Length: 240
Image (cartoon, rainbow, N blue to C red; front, side, top):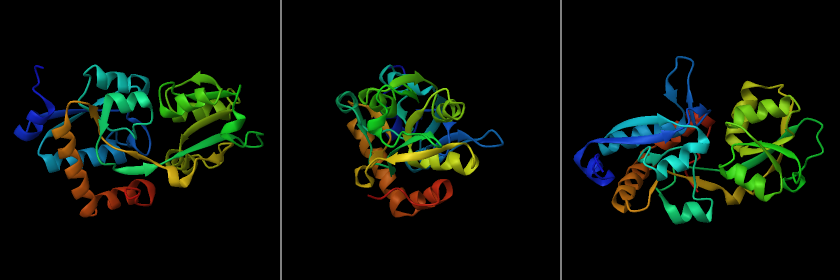
């Protein structure tokens, strides 16, 4: 490509592009002054400094994200992604994880929905191509497409959908901000089966992955991930 390979740009101190939503607190969002921040964004900035590269974030709709990575929209995705499908496993590589977390199911207060087993045939608001959307599909839910978590919760609040799967920490963050929303966590995925999210690249970039993982390991060792997890979640979620 016109850009040179990713490892060339890492080793030669060029520019790396990163896909992220910018609409998913506390991972990747804009603060009250319009600054792009969130755990994944700040981790990525710290990685870029360790590698001596310029970083540019390409804000992207979730349902365009992994397609975008595959089509060259950006070099890397930083957006709470693990290789959670056989397809992702066949197509992409993931750095050392920077965080571990897992899913929960949200329903309206006073719902009869108690489990991922209870969503067959139920209106379940999701981004279609997320791990959550694909799992809702596998569970036999009737999916209602949306642009992510905040809109899915709007639908449940308004009784326009009945459930959603999403990340525990994103849901808890939302409930801190919206403490009488009318929704609740009704089910949790197993705490010992968390997903490790890392920087995602196309296969064929092994050396670049090693550089990302080395940086992430140093940010763990020097306490940066602990600090950033404190800031965004109130706990360090980088170890497992």
